[PDB]
Image 1 (tube, each protein chain N blue to C red):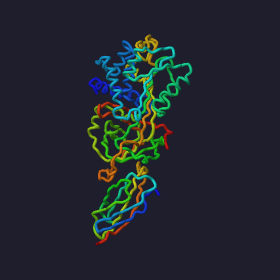
Image 2 (cartoon, rainbow over the protein chains, first blue to last red):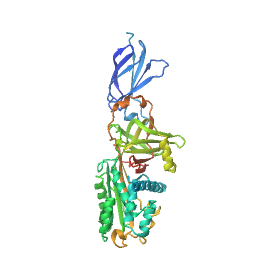
Image 3 (tube, one colour):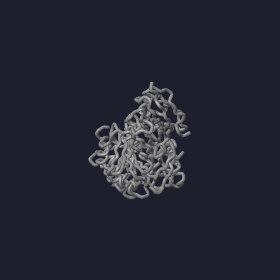
Length: 96
Length: 380
């Protein structure tokens, strides 16, 4: 309950992914969205989104590559050494 | 501020730091909360209702020797009016000042008239016979002045025969960028590394002027208040420790140095949420800085205040309810969708810290204090 849920890709293009999720039970100040090639060397790329939003577009991706997308809810719990609140999915962008 | 009020703003800040340092040396003193202008207006009232060395020592404690008596009362009167400039008057800033004299003492009309104009001073008689009723009159007056935020000044009065000056305040900093009302939870406050109390804390990540002094082991953050008309600066050591070491570094020269090295960075701020109630009797500390005549039962000359030498300064109560709350001005939430907040600095105020509130327009210091021991019953 105190973690984001139903993380899924709603729309996919060779270079982009529109993701959506359902907010956790507690209020979220902002989300950190991290993404990167699954199992690869490259450091993950990340951006923040205000807490009100439940959708995000990830652009600048490579066709037919598998990516690990993590959405972290940042609420009061996460301050002062509190635990991370993540949810992860894997998705292969189309070759189209 | 006018040139005379500007010099007295500098002198009032200088006095508050000397008073803070004298109080920090006392082992019985835990939290400190001083409004430099209210402290200075207390000395101004002693000068207004005092004669010869009783009044000259009041100006000496303020380091205002080369200032005429009219320049002192007019400058301090203008400074008290300027306190409502960065805040919502009688909403986020409430102040009352009352002089309590014994039932057998009548205040001179000349003093009542001038003290009310210069210092908004109220005058009252107090029956020291029943101590329970004399305390209830002072406590009910402070409670009404602050609408219950400061429900009690003191539980006992020591000197029960002279004049009692009581200053009751409520101050609530209204942030330029509010904390969200739901970004609050229960946390631990380390009073020492072996004693932790429970406190409610409020949390937010934003852009703030910040400096981490690695050599002196402390973080310093500036939190602007409404429309940047004032700002609240917090100085907190890296480790939970007594504030004695950091207090030695508390000079205008070092504060100017720390202010110059601050850079606007993303900071994850967590602060205790709630009302901090602090009462000080400044009588013994002001005497220790040069106010020996006014506080002495025999040498005190308060003839301008009552008409006869039948009054001495028994107490100078400085009581404040300083409320840390989430409320402030709204801001664009799209600042959260910006790269700058990627790896914020962590300013987690879960151990003793020094804080100061400064008026940005006049440069005048509004509050100086420290939070060592949060009440212990204000948690949700």
